[PDB]
Image (cartoon, rainbow over all chains, first blue to last red; front, side):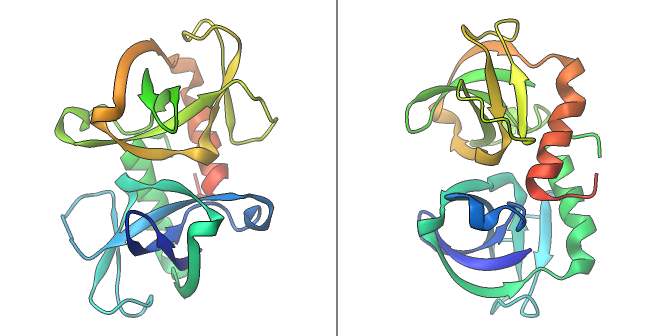
Length: 99
Length: 99
């Protein structure tokens, strides 16, 4: 579950949502952007300087995007495996899925 | 879980992934496109003329996008509630989540 820099509307840190199993086999990748604007939504997952940011930030699961791999840039961090349960929790509530 | 026409790169049918609970409260909406090109991936959910298409089609959960509501168009169908378990199954495998 790596964290790259990606070219969205502008350069932002993103969470690779697409499974790393099939990543070298696809021309596109689904990502979740990371913005410093914390809005206090359930669909957010906190990330901080431990993950690889300057100021504290959040993974915005309501704004997931599938971008070309050409727009995927430097690898700058990782989502800790202890945060994985909350990621599934964020996506399930974001889309109303029966996890 | 409605099915609208949306303006992506071109006009396509889409599955509203964003929960309808918060839909009239957001300027963006996360959708999953529907293409007739069936590739036989686990991350696909079959839809047909019952849902509101001409030829049989599939929900491509590897290409989900968050688009402005301004690009959301006519309501043309519905995802049957019996297909809901497969939708959660498709997204969970698409992102490797512990459903």
